[PDB]
Amino acid sequence: RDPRPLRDKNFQSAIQEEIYDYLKKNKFDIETNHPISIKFLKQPTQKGFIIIFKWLYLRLDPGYGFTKSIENEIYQILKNLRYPFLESINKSQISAVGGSNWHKFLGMLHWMVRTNIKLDMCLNKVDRSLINQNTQEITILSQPLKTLDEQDQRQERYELMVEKLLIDYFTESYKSFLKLEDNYEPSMQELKLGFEKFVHIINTDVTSTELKLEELKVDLNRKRYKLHQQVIHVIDITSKFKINIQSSLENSENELGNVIEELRNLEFE
Amino acid sequence: RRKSILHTIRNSIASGARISLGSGAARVVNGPVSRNQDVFPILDLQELVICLQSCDFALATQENISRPTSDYMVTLYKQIIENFMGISVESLLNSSNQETGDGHLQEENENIYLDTLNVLVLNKICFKFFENIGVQDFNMTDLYKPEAQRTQRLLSAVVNYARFREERMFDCNSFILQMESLLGQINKLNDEIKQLQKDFEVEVKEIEIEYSLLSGHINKYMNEMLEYMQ
Image (cartoon, chains in turn yellow, purple):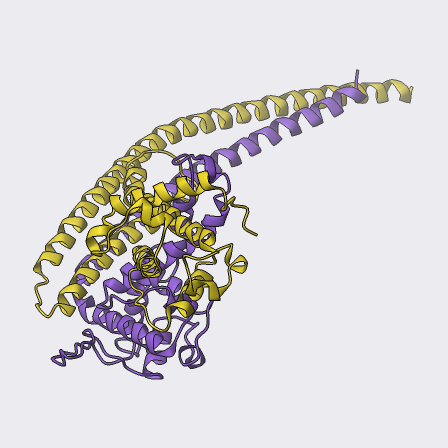
């Protein structure tokens, strides 16, 4: 359905002011010599409607080139854009825009303007996202912490970094290839700088690891020294205990033997 | 992702395929200027399908190019972009969608826009990708109302780009080898350090077990003795 109160005239006034402001801020009147004024938005011509729709959709999808019969293409564009209010609008009405059903058409134009603004915002968001998740790898790779299944993740990150460098090289090189001049030295030197920074980071990491292993070797030797001392002490005490227990048992056995023999002598009588 | 076009090409070099099939590069000049088609082949099926499957793109099948439909080219394009350009389309759309930027009265139902915007973003991504491969002509139709001509055109440009990558690969090993050298060195150091620490701690635990059970046994027999005799 179409919940918009399209028929309200204050709503229409707001929409027409917004559309005028957007087209002026992005120079519709200059790119196409057809001028635009709010009075026109209140009293639209068919040709001006076609021009505005074309301009908006081309700002939304520059690769599209119109063809066919605009009545047949406006519907298909909206269908591909999955315009939620498509089922509420009949195709035939596109023929006479300024007639009875101008409110729905002005509504879709407002829809398109909002979609254009939000699309521009989304593109800025994703561009900043790219530049930020490019630097997340390096900032993560220069922090000391953790050892949990992640050293493999570290190598994966290094590989992805170098792969990004290579992809940049290839894309720029193919640009030169299509633009029939063949100057790969600039791409090559940019790749060289990137890989040099990669090498610096990874070698810093390698030196850290080598120092850490050497320190571990020192510490393990120091600890095994104490381990050996403790084992020797335990063996010493064990042997002393064994000899003392053996001697006590021997003395007890001999004395009990003597007493038993004397008792045998006594009982014989 | 475990795969790529770079490492797969290297693995193919190691194999008997040689350079992963195909005929190197293509660059068509054009002075039809009354007409103009940009600088890349429109190489036809079989060649096109064979090259696509050579790049480890299982979704490539002749029945799709000559009779395309929506939801099929979409997966293939996402896959190609994420392989050659090394990105995640889903992550990018999620980044676009998130919030704490705008806030607006009539935007309490952004859902009616949300879907559409995702579509647009996808499309625009492809645009730039294909804008880098000599074609300025992606638009929506390629994704949602596909036709065989444009499909084969875009795929031909793609395979030409892949062949260019293969050709220029030789300039890259001087870096891949050093990367793998440093990574292998790090891995070996980590394995050695882990082995040493594990050895020491196992030795300590074994000695602790020995002496704890020794104490237990001595107490066992001493007390078993002294209970019977007293």
